[PDB]
Length: 268
Ligand SMILES: [Mg+2]
Ligand SMILES: [Mg+2]
Image (cartoon, rainbow, N blue to C red):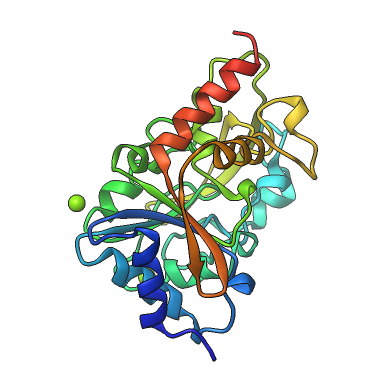
């Protein structure tokens, strides 16, 4: 039987989601199983679980980010520069690789969307505008980003059948860790400024491996290794949401753990 909205809501409360919470979800839809109305049912369930004073923050990115196409160049290659669409937060679809739920989140009425095309975040709830801005180039996941404000806002990470590599907030630990050898990347994004396309080139921390030993394309990256160690070392509520093994994680706690984890292992 397809999972109903009200069944999902009871499971979320069993897991510890309370009215008023600030939740960032990472979802494996195939793990959850058939829903009564497809993925919207789970989006509906999450909005109901956090209530009208609660907030959802999701890492949605952009289906057509020109990250790899501009990676490593001090300007976008001519053919990219001429024809790439400017990022338009009202119409740019979500990146499919983080899960099909994120397109449903970002098109929810009243959803706000942050201005960073590659790191774009969507937020639903009364604090959404405060969560999504500022989001400037060169500050994808660290201080001054939506992840930073989420960590200051009692944020909980809701992993619904997702792996330990999925925890976006740990890129904040990578950004502030006092470790030698931190990898950076250079890329370019096309922004809308007054409705004209403007190409902006920036550097930021490499989010595909903060150090060489974590940059193997198959992993494990540092996010996976930190989260795997954290979950073996911490009491975290675990339970089903739909058919999926799910956990509800204290975001500030896992990020503080990750900062200490990196600084213990790598000289300053
Ligand atoms: Mg909209
Ligand atoms: Mg509030």
